[PDB]
Image: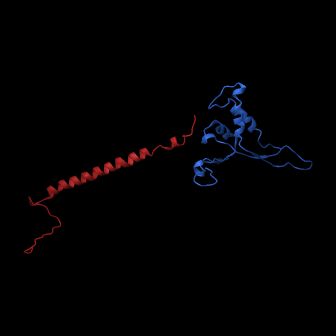
Chain colours: A red, B blue
């Protein structure tokens, strides 16, 4: 603090409506954990299954292009 | 092959045939005018019999031996076509060439996943 400028630095800071903030920060923790879990699920489902399923079977058709039966 | 000499043994023979497929093609060209009915994709009904009649003569017996090399044409790059498919069973070693290897600048364009030998 000094007469022209005032600045206070804090490692962890939030509006202290109560003497504790764990009950408020737990909501953010739940949101972050849920977003991470859903993002992992979405990435896995969108990529791993789908791309492998598309790449599963393509050569049995390419090998028979010139067939006349 | 079956030639002997007085106090002289036999001789080994090498035989080279170029495009044995033209024999069956010429057989095809006259099948309809002889009065037959076509089969498969426009082929004559006696393809296998007249291939085997010729193929069973190119062989080595107790009296003399023959080593032969033949070139087989594959129409329209289709290994499933009846003529090469029928021909496949008359040989001991089969070498298969592929256009995909040839178009990449690799010579000789021999396919290593389709060439077998007894």
Q: Nearer the viewer, residue B61 or B44?
A: B44
Q: Position of residue B110 (x, y in %)?
A: 63, 51
Residue A24 position by quadrant: bottom left
What residue is shown at x 75% (from left), y 35% (from top)? B53
Indicate the position of residue A28 as horizontal and vertical percent values.
Answer: 19, 55
Would you place residue B92 above or below residue B48 in this image? below
Q: Is residue B31 above or below residue A42?
A: above
**Left or right of residue A31, residue B23 in this image:** right
Q: Nearer the viewer, residue A26 or B19?
A: B19
Residue drawn at 71 percent across, 27 percent down = B33
Residue at 51 percent across and 44 percent down: it is A59
- Give the position of the N terminus of chain A as an image quadrant: bottom left
Residue at 45%, 44% in the rendered image: A56
Q: Nearer the viewer, residue B93 or B74?
A: B74
Query: In the rendered view of the protein, which quadrant contains the C terminus of chain A?
Result: top right
Q: Position of residue B69 (x, y in %)?
A: 73, 47
Identify the residue at the far left of this view: A3
Left or right: B22 in relation to A36: right
Where, by quadrant of the figure, is residue B22 drawn? Answer: top right
């Amino acid at each position: 603090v000094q007469p022209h400028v005032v600045t206070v630095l804090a490692d962890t800071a939030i509006r202290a409506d109560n003497l504790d903030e764990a009950a408020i920060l737990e909501a953010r923790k739940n949101a972050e954990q849920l977003l991470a879990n859903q993002k992992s699920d979405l990435d896995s489902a969108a990529a791993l299954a789908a791309l492998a399923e598309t790449a599963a079977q393509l050569e049995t058709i390419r090998k028979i292009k010139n067939r006349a039966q | 092959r079956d030639e002997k000499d007085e106090n002289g043994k036999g001789r080994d023979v090498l035989l080279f045939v170029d495009n044995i497929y033209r024999y069956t093609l010429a057989g095809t060209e006259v099948s309809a005018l002889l009065g037959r009915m076509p089969s498969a994709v426009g082929y004559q009904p006696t393809l296998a019999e007249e291939m085997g009649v010729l193929q069973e003569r190119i062989t080595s017996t107790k009296s003399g031996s023959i080593t032969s090399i033949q070139a087989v044409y594959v129409p329209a790059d289709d290994l499933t076509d009846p003529s090469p498919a029928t021909t496949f069973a008359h040989l001991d070693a089969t070498v298969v060439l592929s256009r995909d290897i040839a178009s990449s600048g690799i010579y000789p364009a021999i396919d290593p996943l389709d060439s077998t030998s007894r």
